[PDB]
Length: 167
Length: 173
Image (tube, rainbow over all chains, first blue to last red; front, side):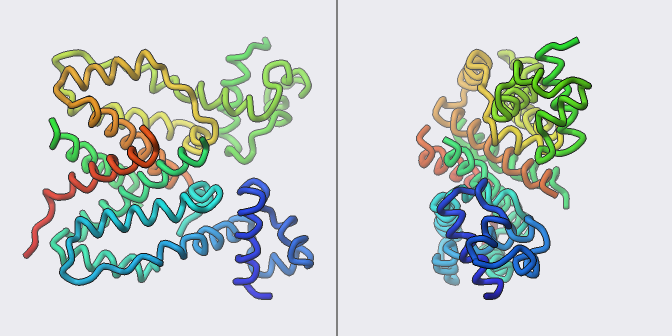
């Protein structure tokens, strides 16, 4: 028993009872251990959830990283389709994702490909946030049935500018 | 004086105060200075209380003027999404409340907004997708700020919109 073991059990438990059934009490019970041993590793419920959300994203890493020279545009579509499938495959995957803060190296790597393909740093960043937040919203709704303002505005302009193109 | 709108308004104020994770019938009862079972008659369950709170939370968005023929559809589009954002941010954990108990949209208002976009020359299918994209994007944005037609098709179209808007900033040099 260590952090990985706890997180793997927690994910099993999420698969079995959905996000609302996930608690430090039920998880300790499951591990055949009492609560303090579990509170060694995660001090709050939100530490646990964060670790689970970070661990639940591992399958997105089944996507090959971009290759130098390849179409940034086709890549960006694949990469976002992968992001959506990851969240969508996991029970309450989007709520798990949205209920915590977040392969940071893997993100920088993908950002460098984008910058090399001629998307300026600021736009690469905004485009990747926009796409992810849109995906979070999309899947959350599917599964039910820091300058945030300037990030919102940049994402919104992307959408609307995409639309202007069909008018 | 006990009154449904009153209870709901008091619940949304409670939400502002304690966070969504702190909203309970017992806590609302106490804010109101009443016996907790007296609230059962308004909201049989916590689920029903939330649904009601989520619906009332949208009123400020519904209070906005509808678009009129002749106005710039482009500026209105931005303005509409800015309104939706502002609405969600107006109550603490506003976007979790929304996402958790999806309110029912005014079909009359949704149709008038859509008609305006179509009469402005936006092709219908694209207007619909844009409108879905814009909303879903705003939920995801606001969720992250505050934390601090089939779904497949809609996802694909909203993603192409985003990626298309990016093309203009691209310069391979």
